Image (cartoon, coloured by chain):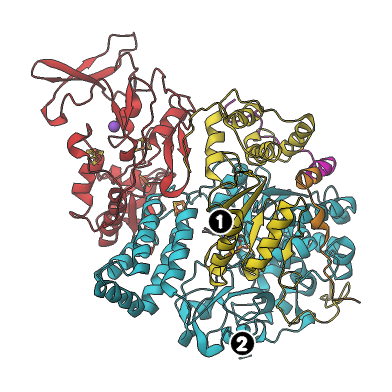
Chain colours: A yellow, B red, C orange, D cyan
Amino acid sequence: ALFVHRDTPENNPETPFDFTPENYKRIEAIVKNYPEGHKAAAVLPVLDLAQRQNGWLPISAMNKVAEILQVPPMRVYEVATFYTMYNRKPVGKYHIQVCTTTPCMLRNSDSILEAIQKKLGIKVGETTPDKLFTLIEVECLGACVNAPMVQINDNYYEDLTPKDIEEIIDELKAGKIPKPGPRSGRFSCEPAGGLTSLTEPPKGPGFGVQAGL
Amino acid sequence: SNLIEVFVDGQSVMVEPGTTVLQACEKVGMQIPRFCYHERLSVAGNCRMCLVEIEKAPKVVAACAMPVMKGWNILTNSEKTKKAREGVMEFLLANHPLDCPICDQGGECDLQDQSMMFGSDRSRFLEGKRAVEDKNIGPLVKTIMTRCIQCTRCIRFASEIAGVDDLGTTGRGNDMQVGTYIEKMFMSELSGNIIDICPVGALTSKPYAFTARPWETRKTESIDVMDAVGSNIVVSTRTGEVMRILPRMHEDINEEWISDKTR
Amino acid sequence: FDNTTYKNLQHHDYSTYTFLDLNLDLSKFRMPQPSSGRESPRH
Amino acid sequence: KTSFGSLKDEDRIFTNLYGRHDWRLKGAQSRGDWYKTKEILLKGPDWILGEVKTSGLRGRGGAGFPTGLKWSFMNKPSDGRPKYLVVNADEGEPGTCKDREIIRHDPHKLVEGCLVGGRAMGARAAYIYIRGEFYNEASNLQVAIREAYEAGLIGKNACGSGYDFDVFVVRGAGAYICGEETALIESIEGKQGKPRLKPPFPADVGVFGCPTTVANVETVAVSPTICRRGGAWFASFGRERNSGTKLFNISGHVNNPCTVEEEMSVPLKELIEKHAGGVTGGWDNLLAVIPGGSSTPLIPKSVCETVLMDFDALIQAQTGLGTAAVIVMDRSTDIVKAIARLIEFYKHESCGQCTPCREGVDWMNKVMARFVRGDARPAEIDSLWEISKQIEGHTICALGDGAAWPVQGLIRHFRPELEERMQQFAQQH
Ligand SMILES: Cc1cc2nc3c(=O)[nH]c(=O)nc-3n(C[C@H](O)[C@H](O)[C@H](O)COP(=O)(O)O)c2cc1C
Ligand code: SF4
Ligand code: SF4
Ligand code: SF4
Ligand code: FES
Ligand code: FES
Ligand SMILES: [K+]
C-alpha cells in the first residue's frame, strides 16, 4: 500500500462523486453532534459515510468531504491515510479480514487463511477476478476468546474451522448472507460445555441497595 | 514578584510562570539539543532530542514542552540525560541515509553536529534502511525525503507562518511520510524558508544545489532591496562570487524569514 | 425464566446505514450544542 | 481474607454478560439497571465521588489508576467551557474482548454509568468512542441510547433530576493507538490518532480544548452499581488497593476460551481451571501466560503456579494486570514466534509521531524476525534489551512501553530458547 496519490482515469479529482440527498440528511445529524465552531470533528464519520455509499474513497470523495466541512483537503488526506478502515482503492463486494495476531494465531488462524486462499484462488491482499472478494490480514479484532475469526464487511464470524469458513464463502458466493457469530455451537463468549457463572436468575430492582439512598 | 525560582545544575534562575525547561536553561546560557522545537513555531514535542532529567524525578521530560515547576533542579549534563540523548540520536540515525558527501546540508547540519556533540560514535544497527520516494513541490525547493526525520517543522511553518495548509503527514508508524499526498506545488512567497527550518538536507534550495560547502563561504551581512521592508540578510560568497542569500535575524523587521524574491 | 437461548439476535438484520439512521433519529433529543464563539479556528 | 475467587452470582455486576436475557431497556430494568437513578443524581457529585473513592475502584482500561481520585480532577467551578466525559470503548489490546460484551449485552449499564459518572464530573455530555470494527455492537448501543432518551432517563431533565445530559456515540476508523486517552481525544476532533504530550492534562484541556475525563467502558459501567450498593460492598472483594470484581478474558491454549467475571486477586491457576476448563493438554503442558493483554510481559509456568490476578501481585511478578486479558501458551508454542507477532502488531499500530517508537519499534520488529529464524548472534540479545530500554520512558505515550515490555519479558524468562535457536541456525550454515 502506498501513501501518495497519483491521478489515473479511474481515480482523479474529476472522478464523479456526491452524497445522495438522503446521505446529506445523515451528514447534517452527524455535524450536529459537535460544538459549534468545531466541525472538523465530523471528518471521520462523514468520510466513512462517503465510503459506505461508494464502497471506497476516490480522491474526489476526499475533496468533497473537505469542501462540505470547510477543512483543508490535506487534513482529510491525513485522516484517510492514517486509519486502516478507509479503502483508498476499490475493494471487492465482500472484504474478508482475517485476524492473525497471537491470540488468534495460537488457535490456528493460519489454517483459516490457507482455507480461504485455496477456495478463492487468491493470495492475501488480492481481489478475485470476479471482484466479489478481497482478502487481507488484520490485527486483533477484539474477539480473541472466539478465535479464530474473520470479519466480512460489518459482520464477525468466529470460532471458525476450514470447513466453516468455506460454507460462509459458499453462502456469500451463492447470494445469501450467513449469520454472524460463533460457528462452534456456543452463542457468544460463554465457556463451551456449559456455563460456569450466571447460572441463577438475576436479582431484581433494589437488590443489595445500600441504606440511605 | 511573579517570578518563580528554579535551578539549572544547582544554579538559581528566576523565570516567569509558563517558562519551559528549555527556556530556563537558555537563561543560564545552556542550549538543550533539539530538532522539532523552533522558538517561532508551535511546540511539537515529537523528536524527543530535548529529554532532560529533573532531580528526584524518575522520568525524563521533554524540555521544549514541559513547563518548569518551582524548585525544580534541571540536570542538563547528568548520566540519565546523556543516555537519553544517545538513545534518541541512535534512533534518528537508524534509517537515515548515508548521504553526507552528496547532501547539501553537510557541514551546516544539525543532525551531523548534534550527533558529534550528544550522540554515540558508532552504529549497532544491523538491518536494512527505509527509503521513501521524493516529492515535487516546485522549482525552488528540492526534496530528498529519505533524509527527512519527521520533525514536522515544515508542516508547522506552512500552516502557521505562511497560512498554507498544504503539507502534512500521510501513513502511520515507520511509513509516515511528510508531503502533500497529491501532486502539488508549495509556491508561496515565504516558501523558501522551509529550507532554513528543515534541520536536515530533506528540503534544500534547488538553485543552490551542489554549488558550495558552508565552511568555505564568506558571510557578508547586508540588507535586502527587493521591497521596502528592508529584511536583514546574509550574502554568502566564495572566491568573489555570490552563492546564495540567507535571512539574518532581526526581531523588529523580518524576524528570521525572507521572501522568495529576496532569497 | 429461560437462560438457554440467545437474546441478542437483532443485529442479524442490521444494514449499512443502521448506525447513522439511529444517530439521525436521535437528533431530535439532543440539547443545543455549545459554541466556541467563531465559525472555526481559522475564522 | 487470604483467599479470593469464588464470586457468587448475586455479587456479579454484569449479569447479562452472555446475552441470555433481553439486553434492551425492559430487561435491563428487570435486572436492576436504572433503579433509583434520580436519587443518586440528587445526592450530588461529592457523594458520588465519595462512593467511587471508598470502593477502591481502579482504572480497568489497562493502567489501573485510582478512579475516584482521577474523576475528582473535574470537580471544580466552571470557567465557561463545557465539561465532557469521554468513554473509551476502543478495545484494541490483543487478547482483550471484555468491553465488547458490555456494549452489546449490558448497554444500559454503560449508558447509566455515563449519566452517573458524568454527573459527578459535572459534564454536559458523554462521548462514547467505540472502535469502528464493532459495527453491530455500536448499533446495539445506539438502540439502547434511543430507548433511554424516550424514557427520559437521559437528555433534558435526566431521570427527573433537573440535570441535562447527552450521550453521543462516535466510531473509530481502525487504529489501536486511538485507545490511548489523548489519541482518542484527537481522533474525536477529526485529526490523526496521535497522542498529546502532558501537561496539559485532559481534566484541564481535553476534547475540543475543554475539561475532559477519559474512562474505560468497564470502569464507567460499574459506577451505578457501586453507588446503589455502596463502595464498602465493592471494597469487600479482593485485596486492599485491589478491590472489586473484574472481567477476565482467557484465550489461547485453553480448553474453553471464554470471558467471565471473577473476584480480584483470584489465583491465576484457579481462574484458568475453574472457568476456562484448564490448559490444553493439562496444567503440565503450560509454557507461559501473558496475564494482562499483549502489553504486559509474559510469565513462565513456575510463576503462574501461585500468582494472584491483581495490580500489586502481578507487578511483583514483574508484569502487570493490564486489561486482565489472559493469553495462554502451552509447551507446543513457538514462544519466540508468538512474541514476534506481538512486536509486529505494535509495528503496525505505532502512530509514528515520536522518534523512539517510530524508529525503535520497527527496529525491534526486524531484530525479532531474525531471532525467530535464529539468524543472529547471542550478543544481539543484550543489544535488543538495551534498545527496548531506550524506547521505554522516552516516548510520548505508553505504546512505546507496551512494545518494549513484551520483548523484555521474553528475554527475561526465555533467553536459552533464543540462544538455542541461534546455535541451530549456525550449526546448519
Ligand atoms: C496504545 C494504547 C491503547 C490503549 N487502549 C485502550 C483501550 O482500548 N481501552 C481503554 O479503556 N484504555 C486503553 N488505553 C489506556 C487509556 O490510555 C487510559 O489509560 C484509560 O482509558 C483510562 O481509563 P480508566 O482509568 O477507566 O482505565 C490504551 C493505552 C495505550 C497506550
Ligand atoms: S541531513 Fe545531515 S546527517 Fe543527513 S545526509 Fe545530510 S549532512 Fe548527513
Ligand atoms: S522535511 Fe525537514 S522540516 Fe519537514 S518534517 Fe522532514 S525533517 Fe522536518
Ligand atoms: S510512542 Fe508510538 S504511538 Fe505513542 S506517540 Fe510515540 S510514535 Fe505515536
Ligand atoms: S487476536 Fe484475533 S480477535 Fe484478538
Ligand atoms: S525538541 Fe523537544 S521533543 Fe523535539
Ligand atoms: K535544510
Residue type for callout 1:
Val
Chain of residue at mark 2: D
Q: Is residue D190 left or right of residue B182?
A: right
Residue D270: assigned label: 2
Q: Kindly identify which residue carries mark 1.
A: A138
Can residue D209 be seen here? yes
Considering only vertical position in the picture, is B147 above or below A161?
above
Task: Work out whether residue B255 or residue D409 is closer to the camera in this orientation and state it.
Answer: D409
The magenta segment is: C23-43
Task: Work out whether residue D272 or residue A153 is closer to the camera in this orientation and state it.
Answer: A153
Disc 2 versus disc 1: nearer the observer: 1
Q: Residue at x 88, y 74 (%)?
A: A204
Q: Is residue B138 left or right of residue B125?
A: right
Residue C7 position, x and y percent, is 84, 66
Residue D192 position, x and y percent, is 54, 43
Q: Is residue B104 left or right of residue B202?
A: left
- Determine the CA span between mark 2 and mark 1: 33 Å
Q: Is residue C12 magenta-colored?
A: no
Considering only vertical position in the picture, is A36 above or below D104?
above
Q: Residue at x 32, y 65 (%)?
A: D384
Question: Number of labelled discs?
Answer: 2
Other-residue count near label 1 (Cα within 10 Å), few / some / many at <14 / 14–19 / ≥20: some
Residue B128: assigned label: none
Can residue D219 be seen here? no
